Image (cartoon, coloured by chain):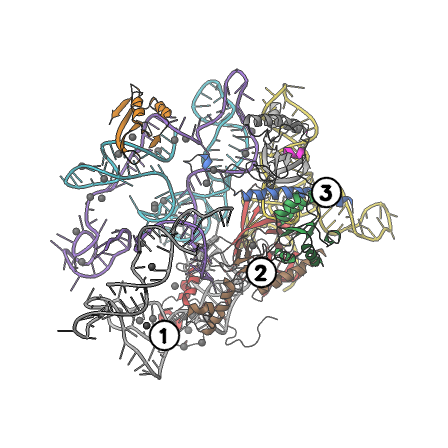
Chain colours: A brown, B red, C blue, E green, F orange, G cyan, H purple, J yellow
Amino acid sequence: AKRTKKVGITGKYGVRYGSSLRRQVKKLEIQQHARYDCSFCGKKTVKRGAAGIWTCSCCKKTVAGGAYTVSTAAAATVRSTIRRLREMVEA
Amino acid sequence: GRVIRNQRKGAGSIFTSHTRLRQGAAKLRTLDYAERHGYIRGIVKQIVHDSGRGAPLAKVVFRDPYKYRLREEIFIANEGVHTGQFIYAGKKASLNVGNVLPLGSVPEGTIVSNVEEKPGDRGALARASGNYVIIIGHNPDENKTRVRLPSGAKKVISSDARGVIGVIAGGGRVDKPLLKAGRAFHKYRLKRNSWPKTRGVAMNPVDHPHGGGNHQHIGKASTISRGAVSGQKAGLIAARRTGLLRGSQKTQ
Amino acid sequence: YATVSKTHKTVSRAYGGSRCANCVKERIIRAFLIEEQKIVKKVVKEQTEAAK
Amino acid sequence: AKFLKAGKVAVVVRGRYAGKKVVIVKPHDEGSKSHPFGHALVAGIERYPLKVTKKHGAKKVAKRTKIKPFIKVVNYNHLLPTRYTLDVEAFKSVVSTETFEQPSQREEAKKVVKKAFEERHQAGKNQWFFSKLRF
Amino acid sequence: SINQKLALVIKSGKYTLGYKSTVKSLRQGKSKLIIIAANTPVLRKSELEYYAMLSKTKVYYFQGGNNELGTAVGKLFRVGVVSILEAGDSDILTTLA
Amino acid sequence: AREITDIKQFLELTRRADVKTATVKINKKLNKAGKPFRQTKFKVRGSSSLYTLVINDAGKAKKLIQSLPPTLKVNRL
RNA sequence: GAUGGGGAAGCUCCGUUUCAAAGGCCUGAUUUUAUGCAGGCCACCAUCGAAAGGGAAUCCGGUUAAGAUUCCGGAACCUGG
RNA sequence: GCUUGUGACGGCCCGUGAAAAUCCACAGGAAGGAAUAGUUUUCAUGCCAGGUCGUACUGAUAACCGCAGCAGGUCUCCAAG
RNA sequence: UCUAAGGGUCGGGUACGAUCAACUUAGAACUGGUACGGACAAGGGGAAUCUGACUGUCUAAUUAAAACAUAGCAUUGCGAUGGUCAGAAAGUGAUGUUGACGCAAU
RNA sequence: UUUACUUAUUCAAUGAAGCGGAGCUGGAAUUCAUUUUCCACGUUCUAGCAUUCAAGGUCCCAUUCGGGGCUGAUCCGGGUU
Ligand SMILES: [Mg+2]
Ligand SMILES: [Mg+2]
Ligand SMILES: [Mg+2]
Ligand SMILES: [Mg+2]
Ligand SMILES: [Mg+2]
Ligand SMILES: [Mg+2]
Ligand SMILES: [Mg+2]
Ligand SMILES: [Mg+2]
Ligand SMILES: [Mg+2]
Ligand SMILES: [Mg+2]
Ligand SMILES: [Mg+2]
Ligand SMILES: [Mg+2]
Ligand SMILES: [Mg+2]
Ligand SMILES: [Mg+2]
Ligand SMILES: [Mg+2]
Ligand SMILES: [Mg+2]
Ligand SMILES: [Mg+2]
Ligand SMILES: [Mg+2]
Ligand SMILES: [Mg+2]
Ligand SMILES: [Mg+2]
Ligand SMILES: [Mg+2]
Ligand SMILES: [Mg+2]
Ligand SMILES: [Mg+2]
Ligand SMILES: [Mg+2]
Ligand SMILES: [Mg+2]
Ligand SMILES: [Mg+2]
Ligand SMILES: [Mg+2]
Ligand SMILES: [Mg+2]
Ligand SMILES: [Mg+2]
Ligand SMILES: [Mg+2]
Ligand SMILES: [Mg+2]
Ligand SMILES: [Mg+2]
Ligand SMILES: [Mg+2]
Ligand SMILES: [Mg+2]
Ligand SMILES: [Mg+2]
Ligand SMILES: [Mg+2]
Ligand SMILES: [Mg+2]
Ligand SMILES: [Mg+2]
Ligand SMILES: [Mg+2]
Ligand SMILES: [Mg+2]
Ligand SMILES: [Zn+2]
């Protein structure tokens, strides 16, 4: 029973702030509230709470991550970059 | 007339910081014997929110080399570090996210955070959520190491200046529209009494260079000299250009 | 708690009224293995020193 | 191999003798009308011989190297089988099903195992066994 | 490939899934080969590894977490360890493993 | 602040150095569902607690009453 | 907000662990004896600042012209020794 | 049902929502301890002591502030059909 | 003044019975000086122009507004031997438990 | 004018803990008589454990229980870095 045609979670803000700002928020909102896969125990049970802090329900691990998403593009590539450079040092 | 606002901030009364809830001060370990001859292990015991800070802190605990006790440090959490992870601090440490190493011991392109300006100052450069620095040079004689800061500026500092592998966590925080006035309100409530902001141009002359007139207007160039004097410097201070920045920025 | 007999302030396992048992199962195994693998680590490289 | 056999050393991993080391002496690999689980009759040590040093003279050494033992029926699922091993001859017959049931029979069992464990420790046979696991 | 072997085992042999039962299997010299998930923690890893060496039981470090190790054995849940006690028509025991 | 039931234990209180006073209370109560019966409560005033022993039994009560220390300072009713 | 300090012609201003030789506990050594030395520690550096924050422990019945979780009655509980 | 208390949950945050005194516990094993009799007061019972100041009443269309027994102002708990 | 629908609790070898307690909603008769949210309680509505986006703010005691704020947008300064600001001075101070996803100034 | 020096002056750090110089061992190194040097010179699967001048070894007290040197842990300069 599809309730809204496009606001979704953003329905809470009614008419205020102007469509476009509500789009932008809706994005990161969806991103931030969503349940994520735990690298460690492998269940999807990582939720947010305070920007950058991502902590896993059962299993109880906490990972520092992006302000509204577990892993951030930049961070990620930096990881891969650090792979590459580390390689250089025992090869 | 009267003392303007931006000179009252200086006596710090209502303008001092709202410190009551903060975890403490983020700093690297002291540059002791271990960290500067070999390395030293720790455990991130907890990563945690700091009121008025973007990025989370990581509580990281170490053994005392000289006494039987635990000594706890307060780190700024690089993205990806997790509770229970082992953190390695030292010249002879290995290059993975979380560990802290002297800019000398990490090759070109290493991406690091919370870096010192002089060795030992326990962390100065790139600490805000998202920011980092990248090593771009080394000069083996007089051990400098060249870096690019988040501002684009490039600086050179001691090769012994410590940094931590990776980028500060919580990035992206500012892509989110604040949406409403109160979300700023609570933001600044846990920072300092800097918000909201009356435009000088809405004040009277007693109040401001910009105040007064029968219409609101600045009445003279709003770009003010460095040699200006307190009570004068409101506007665009020492502004060397002005107007809509067209075309790609980004330092050469 | 100073108005109460000591049995109200522990269980009788090691690390009684302090750590949650499942948690002491844990530190026991870790302790054991790591101390073992420690003997393993030293004889691997005691050999390496004489095999190079 | 079916490692839970007579000689086996294992650290207990639950319950008051938690973290202390034992020896299996008799295994009941599966079953009992009671004890409905794979379980062993073990005789660990409860109060370890304290460290002894040069300074330690005469009857301090006597004092320090006294072991308090103990004997347990115990679930397999609570032992951590060890690579080490210790002989069980001097108390093959002291540690028994029959030994438990009737306390006074247990006290006697421990009595022996104690003299058997202190004998072993002096003239340092099975050296690992007589030293606290820390955690 | 390694997965294809596992699958043959699953459809022609005897296995047990999970941490506790592959210990029943390990204590009882019943296991021929255990297969261990990528992300299953190192204490578990170490403890199975120790249990194994005592039963003279060779081990396989499955590159790929418990999520897939489950799909490996064609189950809709996750598994962190497998214990082969009877290899079916498959040769896993006496191949690369 | 205390109840007691071992008729033996009781007697031991009544001769316990610091037990000067004591009192006996009589209560008409009913039995089960039908009739009534003479309950009696034995209260010994120790120094830091007032022990009270209830003898539901009329018989046991009277034989208990004469058991009391001839030096105890019993309050009847 | 004192203090070693640093400014100020000076009333005083700055600093609060700060470029300071910053202090005190546990018992042992006494069996001239009352307490010197013998260890080992611990280096926390004033102090004021809440009758709504934190915080050892009490209740019912009765009683006065006017007091009561405060008296009386009974029954408790806490801290120290 | 009503008011209040409380639990296990769930929403929210670029906000993630004090401190210290004080109390206990554990890891440690210094050391002190029995058979002619030793250890034990975190079990019970038993003994003594608990100072100083406040404590009435009003708290408001008359006990407070508004020149006053002023239609103004002035923090809060309990709450029947 | 009637009718119907919506529940609890028990024993059943390895279809139902028995009993206790609840206002809700809908339907139908009858009835009156056509009254009935019977007092109390309780939105006037519609079409446009100007103007500020909104919620929020101020001239205590003649102005509540279109004024201020605000999110949003844009510009300026600064890598700490620093930017902005305090102080008669200082081994002085605010930002700063801070570091450009930052602080400061329009 | 340039560019060296460190003791004035200046900045940072630390309950001024491991500096500077030599030496041991290893070893890359290639020997143009033999060493001419350069790097090293106890820790990285694991959310354990690491404290009593340290166990050990060795010398002393006049053998008591206790206890002390040395070594374990290399030398030299007292510039906290
Ligand atoms: Mg402040
Ligand atoms: Mg304000
Ligand atoms: Mg503005
Ligand atoms: Mg404004
Ligand atoms: Mg105006
Ligand atoms: Mg002016
Ligand atoms: Mg002007
Ligand atoms: Mg003007
Ligand atoms: Mg204008
Ligand atoms: Mg208990
Ligand atoms: Mg113990
Ligand atoms: Mg002062
Ligand atoms: Mg006070
Ligand atoms: Mg108070
Ligand atoms: Mg209070
Ligand atoms: Mg009363
Ligand atoms: Mg009176
Ligand atoms: Mg009264
Ligand atoms: Mg009284
Ligand atoms: Mg009394
Ligand atoms: Mg007492
Ligand atoms: Mg209320
Ligand atoms: Mg919370
Ligand atoms: Mg407790
Ligand atoms: Mg001693
Ligand atoms: Mg007591
Ligand atoms: Mg006194
Ligand atoms: Mg009163
Ligand atoms: Mg009155
Ligand atoms: Mg009035
Ligand atoms: Mg019905
Ligand atoms: Mg009809
Ligand atoms: Mg408006
Ligand atoms: Mg409005
Ligand atoms: Mg007005
Ligand atoms: Mg006026
Ligand atoms: Mg208005
Ligand atoms: Mg616009
Ligand atoms: Mg000065
Ligand atoms: Mg130093
Ligand atoms: Zn998890």
The chain carrying label 3 is C
State the extent of the magenta-drawn residues as a range.
D123-132
Instruction: Name the amino acid, label 1.
Output: Gly
What is the tally of numbered marks visible in this picture? 3
- Look at the numbered disc 3 and say if its residue's Cβ is closer than 8 Å to ligand 11: no
Query: Marks 1 and 2, how far apart in space?
Result: 48 Å
Q: Which label number is shown at residue B212?
A: 1
- In the rendered view, does E20 fall on the left or right side of B242? right
- On the image, numbered disc 3 is attached to which residue? C43
- Residue A22 showing in the rendered view: yes
**Which image quarter: residue B195?**
bottom left
Mark 2: few/some/many CA within 10 Å (<14, 14-19, 20+): many
Instruction: Name the amino acid, label 2.
Output: Val
Residue for point 26% across, 32% down: F36
- In the rendered view, does F69 fall on the left or right side of H28? left
- On the image, numbered disc 2 is attached to which residue? B167
Q: Secondary structure at mark 2?
A: loop
Is residue B182 depicted above or below D102 in this figure?
below
- In the rendered view, does B192 fall on the left or right side of J64? left
Q: Nearer the viewer, mark 1 or mark 2?
A: 2
Query: In terms of image quarters, where does ligand 8 lie?
Result: bottom left
- Look at the numbered disc 1 and say if its residue's Cβ is closer than 8 Å to ligand 8: yes
